[PDB]
Image: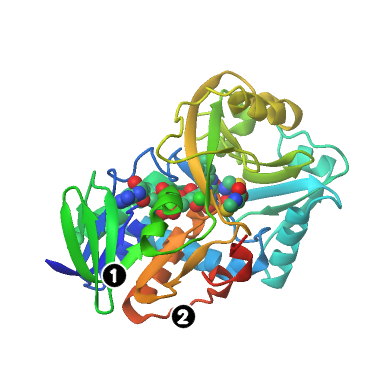
Amino acid sequence: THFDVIVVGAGSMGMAAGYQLAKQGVKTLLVDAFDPPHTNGSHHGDTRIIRHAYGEGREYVPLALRSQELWYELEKETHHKIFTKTGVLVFGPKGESAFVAETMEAAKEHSLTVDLLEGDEINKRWPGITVPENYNAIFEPNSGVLFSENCIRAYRELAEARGAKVLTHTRVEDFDISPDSVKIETANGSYTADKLIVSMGAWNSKLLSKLNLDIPLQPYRQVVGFFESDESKYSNDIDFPGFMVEVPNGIYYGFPSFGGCGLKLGYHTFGQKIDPDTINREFGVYPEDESNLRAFLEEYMPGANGELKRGAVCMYTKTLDEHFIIDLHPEHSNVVIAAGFSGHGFKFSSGVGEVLSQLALTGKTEHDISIFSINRPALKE
Ligand SMILES: *Cc1cc2c(cc1C)nc1c(=O)[nH]c(=O)nc-1n2C[C@H](O)[C@H](O)[C@H](O)COP(=O)(O)OP(=O)(O)OC[C@H]1O[C@@H](n2cnc3c(N)ncnc32)[C@H](O)[C@@H]1O
Ligand SMILES: O=C(O)[C@@H]1CSCN1
Ligand SMILES: O=C(O)[C@@H]1CSCN1
Ligand SMILES: [Cl-]
């Protein structure tokens, strides 16, 4: 079969693209090194935050809101759980967080529904949080938590029912791009199509050279821990929120306990530089894994600092400016690139799937994706 479209990397972005293409009757092949969802890429550890008011930049808000609507649509189409509306709390020291400030500006610019709180008002509203009196906060009630492995599994099952094919456990090794066709090479055979979408996550850093691209991309080792917590404070059932917060030593994020799983925490602004083929995927092999998490919990969420119940090891892929790459290949209009999601892409994957399908089919998108241009100056050293 010569396909209409081949997607290389059927993860967060690729599987969403495959769903969008299959739903329009486009003959699609997706090829993945593993069998998504899996624990070797960037999409595991159960849960992902979706925010609308966006501290990385107000220009992301439209894509977040579209993505949110697409997640509700997915919820209605599958039996897997997709989204729970935890709300998202953002806080930091007053006057000392650009992230908090931009979150607040984004909410104002897009007339988002948020609550503003400070100091003891935070600790009063959410028993279990203990911030200093000089902290301030913005709480977004209508954002929340995605079950990311379920998202990918649902998109996969829906796409496959519509005739998409998923070739699993198959690494793409090389590419051959012509003006009117694309070709991939694998140990399980070679495949051709009219259009290519490249969405290989951390492996984009190693394999985009085979498309003659030289773009700084650094994979990072990013751990999360689940901790035994006071369920009377930290459970989703008592409205404990998702959160993403700035403190003097960086940004931390986390999740309420769901069904007694424990509060989940990660440290966002620090991780080890790694190669995705040699990363150590065991939690706790570095002392920082657990210690950086307990340093936050004992200070700010002291009843969520019990026994470590579970750990996970996942990867970010950062650009120099920490903005995504979503664009056509500059020399090949039949090749679409999705890369560099810099630790904050999952929430957009529904919307990005739609963009990637538009770019593959038409060479354009209705979305404004200027900030993710592959030709922008700030990508380069
Ligand atoms: C690691 C992580 C990320 C993260 C997060 C916490 C952690 C610990 N918290 C987030 C959050 O709360 N909210 C959010 O919006 N994002 C958050 N992130 C980031 C997010 O998870 C990532 O930005 C996103 O998952 C990136 O998706 P992408 O589609 O780029 O990556 P992937 O899901 O890993 O999929 C890539 C696939 O490609 C396959 N692959 C790799 N090499 C090949 C070859 N050669 N051939 C074929 N397939 C290939 C991989 O197997 C994978 O399935
Ligand atoms: O380490 C980093 O964040 C950057 C991302 S691309 C090259 N180095
Ligand atoms: O993108 C987000 O919302 C989360 C919080 S920092 C890690 N990812
Ligand atoms: Cl990432």
Q: In the drawing, does residue 117 fall left or right of residue 333?
A: right
Whether residue 187 is visible: yes
Q: Which residue is mark 1?
A: 177
Q: Residues within 10 Å of mark 1 (few under 14, many from 20)?
A: some
| Residue 232 picture quarter | top right
Label 2 element class = loop
In contact (CB < 8 Å): disc 1 and disc 2: no
Disc 2: CA contacts within 10 A as few (<14), some (14-19) or many (>=20)? few
Q: Residue at x 66, y 59 (%)?
A: 56
SS type, badge 1: strand
* Residue 204 x/y as whole percent: 42, 54
Quote the CA–CA distance across marks 1 and 2.
Answer: 26 Å
At 80% across and 37% down in the image, what residue appears? 131
Quadrant placement of the N terminus = bottom left
According to the image, label 2 marks what residue? 366
Q: Locate residue 272: give its quadrant.
A: top right
Quick one: 55 or 168, which is closer to the camera?
168
- Give the amino acid at mark 2: Glu
Relative placement, left or right, of 197 versus 125 is left
Q: Is residue 88 above or below residue 22?
A: above
